[PDB]
Image (spheres, grey):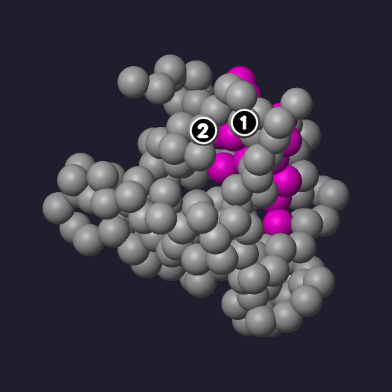
Amino acid sequence: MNTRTIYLAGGCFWGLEAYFQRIDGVVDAVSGYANGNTKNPSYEDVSYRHTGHAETVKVTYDADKLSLDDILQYFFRVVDPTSLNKQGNDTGTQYRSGVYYTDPAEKAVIAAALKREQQKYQLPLVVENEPLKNFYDAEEYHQDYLIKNPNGYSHIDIRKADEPLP
């Protein structure tokens, strides 16, 4: 099938990953560390050694089922686009919001989506929109975290993924 990939930073990746996996059209969702200052960081490097990476979820979707905009709408449904370095109770640059792309043509598409989303908010949007500089997969215990630990922490109501797009 014709697949495409987009990188989404929306806070603790456990919840965001679990969320995207429930959506029909999403064939894979990998948690990792993106746009940091170092290569191959560990969870401890990011969380405690200020490498600067953002917890990100690499989303691979069926280009014939979902468009980049559909993916962005699902993103906006559960991520607060107005808070800087903070989602839920999680604070720090590793929880900053952002959309990172590998195709330069996607920049304009992402910006247009953000402009439209701004009409729903009085506070200014602070979601990042820039090229993916680097991405490194998180350790295995982090992948499918909430599936392995049903009682694990989540700042997102994963159920909301079931709502159909307007």
Which residue lies at the image location 70% right of the left edge and 35% below the top edge?
3
User: Residue flagged by tag 1: what amino acid is it?
Assistant: Ala
User: Residue flagged by tag 2: what amino acid is it?
Assistant: Ser
Asked whether residue 27 is drawn in magenta, I would say: yes
Q: Position of residue 135 (x, y in %)?
A: 71, 63
Mark on residue 67?
Answer: 2
Magenta segment range? 16-32
Asked whether residue 112 is drawn in magenta, I would say: no
Mark on residue 121?
Answer: none
> Residue extending furthest left?
122
Which residue lies at the image location 85% right of the left edge and 49% below the top edge?
140
The answer to whether 143 appears left or right of 24 in the picture is right
Above or below residue 162? Residue 149 is: below
Quarter of the view holding residue 21: top right
The answer to whether 35 appears left or right of 110 in the picture is right
Q: Position of residue 33 (x, y in %)?
A: 68, 63
Q: Position of residue 160 (x, y in %)?
A: 45, 26
Tag 1 and tag 2, C-beta contact below 8 Å? yes
Q: Position of residue 157 (x, y in %)?
A: 48, 32
> Residue extending furthest right?
140
Which residue lies at the image location 72% right of the left edge and 46% below the top edge?
30
User: Nearest the camera: 141 or 125?
Assistant: 125
Alpha-carbon span between mark 1 and mark 2: 6 Å
Above or below residue 8? Residue 59 is: above
- Residue density around tag 2, few if under 14, some if 14–19, many if 20 or more, within 10 Å: few
> Residue extending furthest front?
105
- Residue density around tag 1, few if under 14, some if 14–19, many if 20 or more, within 10 Å: some
Mark on residue 63?
Answer: 1
Secondary structure under tag 2 reads loop
User: Nearest the camera: 22 or 46?
Assistant: 22
Q: Count of labels shown?
A: 2
